[PDB]
Amino acid sequence: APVRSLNCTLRDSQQKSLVMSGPYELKALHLQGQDMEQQVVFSMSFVQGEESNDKIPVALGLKEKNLYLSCVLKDDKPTLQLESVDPKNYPKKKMEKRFVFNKIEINNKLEFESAQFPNWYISTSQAENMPVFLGGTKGGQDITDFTMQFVS
Ligand SMILES: CCOc1ccc([C@@H](C)N)cc1
């Protein structure tokens, strides 16, 4: 049947919000009140891939945009990018591996591991207005835990 998707926002464990701030750019910053309209709304699709109770393969598209988070090698490093797709063909259940994240529930938080690059995670910095990047450890100064808010 059709791929199933939910609208949602994400916040890092320091309660920073994600924003489209530049052509293909996601950054994280502290937001509250009127400025919260600026946050990115995701369409989280539940896609094909290896699955367990606490590890669920998803794709993260921007709501009603043909843009997806994806993991590719750039200048020889696993990186996080926003990638445009053919809007006639997306979302789909069999998303290509660069678009797949394992959504992992640990201690009431979520982590998003790259399916393509094991043990590389969607991450945010301590500091305000830095890239949303792919980080090669769920351990240190960088933030790899999030909460999800469900949106209408
Ligand atoms: C989701 C990707 O967001 C990015 C934000 C910033 C940058 C640098 C290159 N300006 C790269 C990606």
Image (cartoon, rainbow, N blue to C red):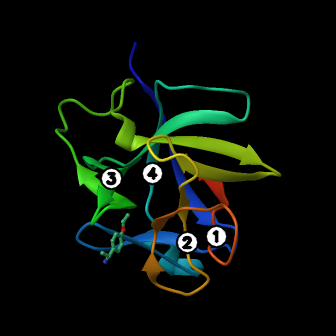
Real-space CA distance between mark 3 and mark 1, rounded to the nearest whole angstrom = 20 Å
Residue drawn where x is 55% and y is 62% of the image: 136
Q: Are marks 2 and 1 in contact (CB under 8 Å)?
A: yes
Mark with earlier residue (3, 1): 3
Query: What amino acid type should be assigned to the residue bearing mark 4?
Result: Phe
Residue behind mark 3:
72
User: Is label 3 or label 1 in front?
Assistant: 3
Residue drawn where x is 16% and y is 38% of the image: 86
Tell me where residue 103 appears, x and y as whole percent.
Answer: 60, 43
As displayed, is residue 30 above or below residue 40? below
Query: Any mark on residue 42, and which?
Result: 4
Residue behind mark 2:
124
Query: What amino acid type should be assigned to the residue bearing mark 3?
Result: Val
* Element type where label 1 sits in the image: loop
| Left or right for 93, reference 104 | left
User: Is label 4 or label 2 in front?
Assistant: 2
Real-space CA distance between mark 3 and mark 2, rounded to the nearest whole angstrom = 18 Å
Tell me where residue 40 appears, x and y as whole percent.
Answer: 43, 62
* Element type where label 3 sits in the image: strand
Mark with earlier residue (1, 4): 4
Residue drawn where x is 61% and y is 26% of the image: 51
Query: What amino acid type should be assigned to the residue bearing mark 1?
Result: Ile
Figure quadrant, ligand 1: bottom left
Query: What amino acid type should be assigned to the residue bearing mark 2?
Result: Thr
Query: Any mark on residue 133, and which?
Result: none
